[PDB]
Image 1 (cartoon, rainbow, N blue to C red):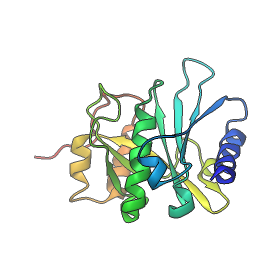
Image 2 (cartoon, one colour):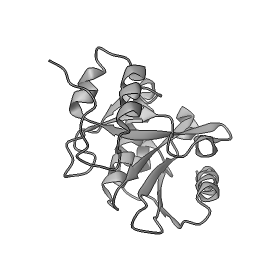
Image 3 (spheres, helix red, strand yellow):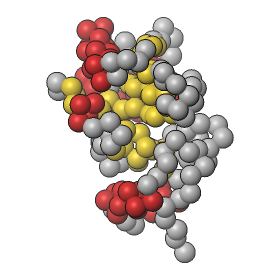
Length: 182
């Protein structure tokens, strides 16, 4: 509800003290029945060399975590994606845990080929963002289609090693895959 959403907003505002943050709500849609008062918060860049961050608010009251997307540009695609994930996480909470992949059902942004996220610790931001009393903030990291397939026969730890070693640019909608299979 409102009090919980304000706790999330305060948490984000404290972490990004000098950024404007916009909140979004629904008065129509899956949200209204399935997760009343759910919000998305948008952390707005101060300059062209900074990304946009979209953060859920409301999932953590049931799941113990919220999720965020780091985007190279402004797009309501992420608002739409997070509403879909709010519904999915209420139905299938076991699939919305660290180390799980999320099938977006479409590219994360239109021109990318990446259709999955890997639910990750918030490596770009650290522990000050990760924890807020009773609730954690996990990163929806886009992964390539071949990376997703790789996770069927290899661990998340192995993939995360490949990510560290490549130094993946998670803001590049066309970054190279870090894995190849025969």
